[PDB]
Image (tube, rainbow, N blue to C red):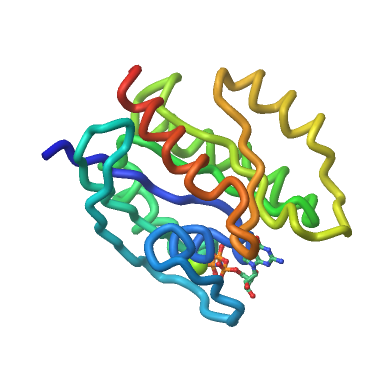
Length: 166
Ligand SMILES: Nc1nc2c(ncn2[C@@H]2O[C@H](COP(=O)(O)OP(=O)(O)NP(=O)(O)O)[C@@H](O)[C@H]2O)c(=O)[nH]1
Ligand SMILES: [Mg+2]
């Protein structure tokens, strides 16, 4: 079957792993549990296509940048995740995008901008600004909550659809 190699990237603590686990295991990890590198594989049906999601969950930490090149290079699609209550994470997005373009030798890699933690009242990043950014990239912006599961399948399935259209 078709396999889709999705990579989840972003700053430390934005909820990359919480999003992935919510997708694969339908629960919200409300734990402190920093990632080094995790992989998940799940057979799904998306729009009637039987396929395998190969999801690489990456570290937000600066120390793991080398293994970051390695993982990025094999990815077909990237979820670029920030937290809507953390302005630095949103600013860091630019640098993850640029590193993906560099390792992939590509200006237009399948990608979704994901604004996570939208369940939180204490927003510092407006939806308007994140949308403008995504528009300037030529990529969809999806807002998610790993906690309530809002937008979770949306973000992953939209990325699969971007890979199909590439
Ligand atoms: N309210 C809320 N909290 C969330 C959400 N997603 C993650 N969190 C919380 O934020 C913290 C970090 O999430 P986690 O999934 O470990 O983030 P990460 O990006 O994988 N961290 P790392 O880069 O270290 O692997 C956890 O305590 C988690 O419960 C969300 O959508 N809403
Ligand atoms: Mg993690």
